[PDB]
Amino acid sequence: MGKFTQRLSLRVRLTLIFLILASVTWLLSSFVAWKQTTDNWEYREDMALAIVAGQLIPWLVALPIMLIIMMVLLGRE
């Protein structure tokens, strides 16, 4: 497998998607754990308009990342 040899943001395909997918899942978990309060099994914790934003933030950024991951293989995203 490659990616590590190239280490230029992105280059390979299929592997990077899985890697990022796992990274996103882990990130989401870390985010869920990263609870905020004051100043500036579980699954669905009682919250008004925060959990959605927390989940959305990484999603909005991850979405393009995935596209870029796949696009990089073509030549450029």
Image: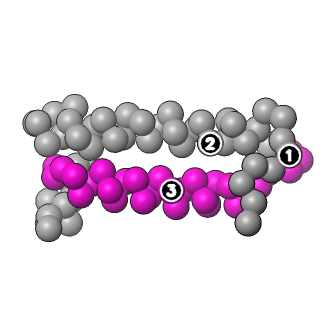
Tell whether position 18 is magenta.
yes
User: Would residue 58 appear left or right of 55 to someone viewing this image?
Assistant: left
Color encoding of the figure? one colour
Query: How would you rate the neighbour count of disc 1 (Cα within 10 Å): few for under 14, some for 14-19, many for 20 or more?
Result: few
Q: Nearer the viewer, residue 4 or 22?
A: 22
Q: How far apart, in angstroms, are the residues tagged by discs 2 and 3?
A: 11 Å
Q: Residue at x 44, y 58 (%)?
A: 23
Q: Quadrant of the N terminus?
A: bottom left
Please state which of the two labelled residues, at mark 2 or mark 1, is closer to the viewer.
Answer: 1
Query: How would you rate the neighbour count of disc 2 (Cα within 10 Å): few for under 14, some for 14-19, many for 20 or more?
Result: some
Q: How far apart, in angstroms, are the residues tagged by discs 3 and 1?
A: 21 Å
* Amino acid type at image mark 2: Gln
- Numbered disc 1: secondary structure: loop
Q: How far apart, in angstroms, are the residues tagged by discs 2 and 1?
A: 14 Å
For residue 1, the mark is none
User: Would residue 21 appear left or right of 51 to someone viewing this image?
Assistant: left
Query: What residue sits right under mark 3 in the picture?
Result: 25
Q: Within the image, what quadrant is residue 18 found in?
A: bottom left
Disc with the residue nearer the chain's start (3 vs 1) = 3
**Extreme-right residue of the structure:** 38
For residue 55, the mark is 2
* Amino acid type at image mark 3: Thr
Prevalent SS, magenta region: helix
- Numbered disc 3: secondary structure: helix
Q: Residue at x 26, y 43 (%)?
A: 69
For residue 46, the mark is 1
Disc with the residue nearer the chain's start (2 vs 3) = 3
* Amino acid type at image mark 1: Asp
Q: Residue at x 71, y 54 (%)?
A: 43
Tell me where the magenta segment starts and ends, as one range: 11-39
**Does residue 41 lie above or below 67 as drawn?**
below
